[PDB]
Amino acid sequence: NDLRDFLTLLEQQGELKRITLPVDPHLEITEIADRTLRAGGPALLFENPKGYSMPVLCNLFGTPKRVAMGMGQEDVSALREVGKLLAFLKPTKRLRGAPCQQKIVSGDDVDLNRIPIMTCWPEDAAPLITWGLTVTRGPHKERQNLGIYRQQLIGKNKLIMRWLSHRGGALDYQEWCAAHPGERFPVSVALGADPATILGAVTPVPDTLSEYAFAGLLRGTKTEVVKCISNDLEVPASAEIVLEGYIEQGETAPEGPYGDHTGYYNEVDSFPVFTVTHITQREDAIYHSTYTGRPPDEPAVLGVALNEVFVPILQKQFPEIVDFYLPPEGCSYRLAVVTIKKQYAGHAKRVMMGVWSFLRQFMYTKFVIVCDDDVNARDWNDVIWAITTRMDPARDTVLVENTPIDYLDFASPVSGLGSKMGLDATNKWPGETQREWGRPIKKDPDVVAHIDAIWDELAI
Amino acid sequence: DLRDFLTLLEQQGELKRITLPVDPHLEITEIADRTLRAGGPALLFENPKGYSMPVLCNLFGTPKRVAMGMGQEDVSALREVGKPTKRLRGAPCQQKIVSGDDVDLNRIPIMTCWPEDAAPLITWGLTVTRQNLGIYRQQLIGKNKLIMRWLSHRGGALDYQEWCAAHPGERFPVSVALGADPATILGAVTAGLLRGTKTEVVKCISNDLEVPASAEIVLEGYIEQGETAPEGPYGDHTGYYNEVDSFPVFTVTHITQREDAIYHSTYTGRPPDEPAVLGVALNEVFVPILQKQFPEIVDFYLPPEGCSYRLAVVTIKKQYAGHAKRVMMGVWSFLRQFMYTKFVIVCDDDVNARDWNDVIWAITTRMDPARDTVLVENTPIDYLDFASPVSGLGSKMGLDATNKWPGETQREWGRPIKKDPDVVAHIDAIWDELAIF
């Protein structure tokens, strides 16, 4: 039901390790988690962080298996069904009491320095909160947005709220300033909610229902919430820790530099300040954290699982698509491989244009490789094979200039604007070539199946 | 010798004996393909369906095992190559003999590699014809007939062409050796002293040609002048079937073998395969020749998955704006072996050329595709590459994935995240006691 249930389950299955040695939240936890993630190991619970009593949980979603379990299922394949659900969509139980409100502190007594907030990389400006569910409401509307923004520590009761312009929290704030000049903007942040509510924030959800409602569908049951002490926002009742407060209009601060998911430092830049009035927590509270850096990291593993959700949405629109994959090594979204059952000359070009335009998540995707269905999109041995035996580079490469690009991608010529490349690695049909194309080597499916059957008894 | 080599590999967990019945028709290839693709061991099939002779394959399926076969622990010593034989009288390879009507090639577990291959095919024969050594594929067309597929430029074909001109009508003597010791096998690539001590050989029973004494099996015979046959189709190292074509016939008069002989085999197909892994190890010879001409080059690698020569990754210590372009042009013009290389990626020295995780990282964080991609049209291409628009002629692509300097960009380029060496060392020290697994 809640996060602790999830952790005891993981522990029985050898998917959680408790660590009793002293480990510093300054740089050391990150190093340990990075080595662990890179070898597919368990989630980690640091019971003795140097200089703090609250234990630190991280690497929670570091294998795609653990992502699936957090949505109820046993294997990664079942994410495709959550996909069909999302296509289909064009409730919440309020409690009076709640574990997340067992211990309270406010006003002058707020001291964020009692929490083991991590510092991830050697040149990061300061400790940084990374797994907060930020809850906001706009002025014209009842819907509550949930968002995951990084928050730098600048004082005993001050954090910076780094939301980028396009995201729901930033839009709610921008409207609030316009509709209520001068008024404090109410905000709350929840740390350590249950896995379904966490995974629901991460997933894109059409406006026809709320974010808490979706998470209720992944979980058998309705999402339980509780009203905040100092505002009318609703937060998950079993949260381990909750921060309540406001944004004072026109108060801002320099943020960063911080290491990012691309493997480089973002340079310094201004964002609004979040003043914390209340810290509420559970009785033996656990602090939930993570880090971004050179891929693969936990976010990148989440993004791989989350791309299985989208395969079906794509297929419904383009039934020619057999598989669709974004390697984590390409910073999760910058490169895609697509395999199709080709039906006509030029077909690959319509598929490129589809990837670059149908879903917003792929709007900034710089490289797209298209292949036939005799290629396993998830294996570089096949993908390189196809590129080097089915392309003439000048004939089969598509370039498009002056297209939208992430403003923090320093590799484009001007901020926000750059080019894209599609590679048509499909077999060329008459009209596309005047040569006799080669007949590929196909395996015998009967021999393949016989070897699957004796594979274990061969014991190699 | 070969058996010494195999017992060494076995004690180091680099050889699996397999006792289950398995067919040389298609099944061995499937098993070897899966094992190679996961970096597993060499394989010795002790019980091949319908044969007594065991089948050895995937011998050189990791570059480590190539190194061990040349004596040492690293492939490094090939970079120094970058910068006479002993005749025995008597030999294990001649312990058992068969000739004339008794020659029956169907007693040998010759593999059929892919479903539409014309027939069983011999793939690791050392063909002997000064003596030239060559590795030519040989299709089985009868009890004592094989097709000898050598293309015109190669040493065996040239010897034969001269023989027909100098001795009209005379039978051409030929021999083929299977399962020689690892050094003579690796030796190739236009005599090789990887071993350092001289190679041991033995005269053939029915001709004056010399073959390795520690061969498991030897075929002796001749080419009857003007006798030819349709060959193939066969699956090849590109991953496609080559179409049918005519080549000379090799009549086998004698089969000589060792007692308890082992049949050494392999397969070519969609890369990577064993030949491709050999070609990667063997390319290390050229790194030094490139470096002497372009000392900026730190590494230079051609993945097997690109059919051994069609794609190259190069890492450099960049010294000026535009530097990557000169290096591209160098790869495409300095050595003839890289004349047909279609794709070239250039990266900085913080990248391991041999790891796709690094190479994709660089491409997706240091390139604007239109600015940084170089296309050149109407350049020389292999005439058998059906993907070019016209036979013998096609385009090439260079990708400049280096960090961009002032002039190449007007933006603030990213500072990469470096780790704290003191934190790394402390975690090495407590790693075992942390006990995560």
Image (tube, coloured by chain):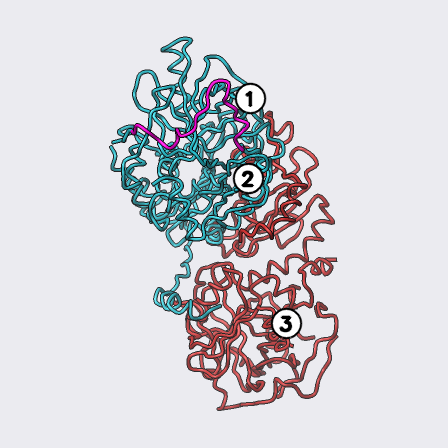
Chain colours: A cyan, B red
What's under tag 3, amino acid-wise? Pro
Instruction: Kindly identify which chain the residue marked by label 3 belongs to.
Output: B
Residue B182: mark: 3
Disc 3 or disc 1, which is closer to the eye? Answer: 1
Q: Please give the name of the residue rendered at 42% of the width and 53% of the height, measured from the top-left corner.
A: A13
Query: What separation in Å lies between label 3 and label 1 (alpha carbons)?
Result: 69 Å
The Cα–Cα distance between marks 2 and 1, rounded to whole angstroms, is 28 Å
Q: Nearer the viewer, residue B425 or B315?
A: B425
The answer to whether B396 appears left or right of A175 in the picture is right
Callout 2: residue from which chain? A
> Circle 1 sits on which residue?
A155
Q: Picture coordinates of residue A7 (x, y %)?
A: 42, 45
Q: Residues within 10 Å of mark 2 (few under 14, many from 20)?
A: many
Residue B129, can we see it? Answer: no
Magenta residues, start to end: A95-116
Q: Which mark is residue A294?
A: 2
